[PDB]
Length: 278
Ligand SMILES: CC(=O)OCC[N+](C)(C)C
Image (tube, protein in one colour):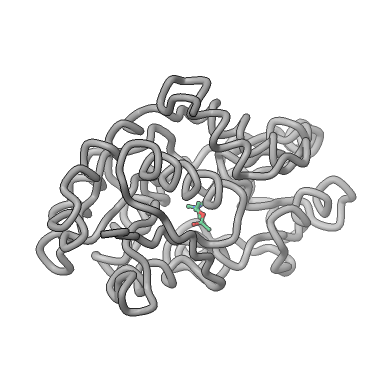
């Protein structure tokens, strides 16, 4: 039959690694072949693509974050525990879109606000509220995802009354260079970022609990499951197989050591026995 499915990803390190793992798992454990589609734009492009589906110049599968689905359903930022966010997006995406959330991969790749350790020491910063009190002295460098998202800086700024001198929209790797050079003093470090535990930075505490959980999980069209039911158990073989620490190390293999994400993804799966060597 030569059936194929389309796995989509935004172009960023973690997204392409986990999309590749999904692709490798499908090709290793089923007869299906996988088109890897890369999307440019924000955290909405994959959602609109999966509504279209692989037969309609969209995608069939991608790895989504629970908190993004939660804020999209609610229309307002909220906080809840991981199960609250996961069960809510799973039930709602099935009802409204016939999209199936599979099990979480294991890590929570949340937004953070992060400063240099020395700045945190110079002002005894521990929390977002501590930072807000001195924010009028500081420049924020952040990803376009953070600056444009409803769950990002817009709602965060209003809750804490952040007063940064200005914000600079920056590519993901650039923002680490920028804080290192003191071009900015705060960045939206993401919890799994490969360069994070490598730059002498302090992650501050979200003391008012603005952000939702951001647990990554594969999601798939129901009609693709209807045609290839084996995909559910195959993709759920990834369930809880990637801790925060594991994801950070894979991200660093790409961003810090220059390895290509296809090789990084496949070697991880082989090392953990999730695929066998052919
Ligand atoms: C681009 C993207 O989807 O990144 C997911 C991580 N997060 C929640 C910090 C934005």
